[PDB]
Image (cartoon, rainbow, N blue to C red; front, side):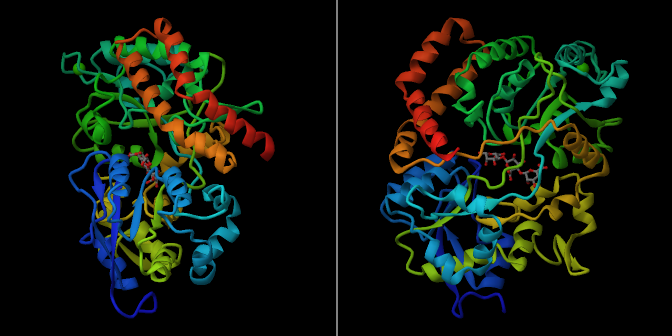
Length: 489
Ligand SMILES: O=C(O)C1=C[C@H](O)[C@H](O)[C@H](O[C@H]2[C@H](O)[C@H](O)[C@H](O[C@H]3[C@H](O)[C@H](O)[C@H](O)O[C@@H]3C(=O)O)O[C@@H]2C(=O)O)O1
Ligand SMILES: [Ca+2]
């Protein structure tokens, strides 16, 4: 083909483990199409049965028989760290000489290129570049509001009242107290509930991210506002307003809790969450989620903390052991070209989409399925966190008119907080970040889970928490980031 990057079929070994559940699959329809178009085939050497993607990365890197390519989600920091240590090769020259689509992309998106570079100036991975503006929003069961003769909640006091009514007043009508007012497929969203009491939970679409407040680098989970917000979240969990299994239900929470007519309220992405309106029309009579503006928080503001990232901390890299770096960067380049963006965004021609008027258009069966289109695509190897350039037109096609009115409402309302994009640390500053931040984050999450589940009291353990943050190096990390901030700005 005209899109081939090599004349002889080339097989590369990839270690890709993502979202704690999935691996590259050469027998994916999209992987087969990838091979057809590029003449490069990726063979997985990852453990399909393993259940923690970050631990699989760590194991593989420690094991001495490195693959040719490493890919996955939440690997930016490790791509940079181990790139500098020489396990991943710098891509700057390879891109300049052999990857015209990536080169053009970075030229038009210099902020993205700057955001993925290591302190030594090297590019150690090609990223997942999202396309879009908003990410999550709030959704509530309008049919339950109607049955209970309640209005959509305008503020946090009204939200509490409405969730309490969902809990206590049997809106699914079975005479059982089985309603679970707040559910979420991302456990981390339980902490984002602190927004309703004027506390940040994150500076970005990455959970538990740093943020900038009045020229100061802060971590949201270290602030007293977070302490006070978490007291409210713990009380909601105690009262059963939050899914008891919020920390373990995970990916199919909507299918289980909306499909089972148990859930009343969530914070999740506009396109896929609103698909459940048509998806459940048959099996759950009357089901209707509506987007609502964030209920006014305790400080008088409507917050949407989440936003679409300019670039995600995901993608793939070329290892030092890869004997075909030129073919590999050309293969990478395919996913920033139109033919490669088609399959990585839309799937396989004649299976999920067709070219019509020169553009990829999803088939009717795809657009009508109760399964959200991005889930359909995951199952065949598209919309996966390789290095690729996402195309928002894929998403437009299954964004319902009602979902779009929600998006436009959030844009017009200016609810969406601008995200933290990072600071430009030196090698020595980032080394402190590398030393401490993962340990701190793990400690934070464990404490937060205990607070939510009520096994630790927030007020009674806050001093210990702060002592721990200090001896685990959080404030050293903040110091380093503040230094980088002060130079930058
Ligand atoms: O659901 C949508 O409407 C939607 C539209 C966009 O086109 C993307 O497909 C978007 O994908 C999201 C997805 O909804 C999840 O939020 C996912 O979260 C994963 C995180 O990216 C990290 O990988 C985390 O460690 O795991 C999360 C997970 O496993 O769910 O992120 C994708 C994405 O950003 O592409 O959804
Ligand atoms: Ca009930």
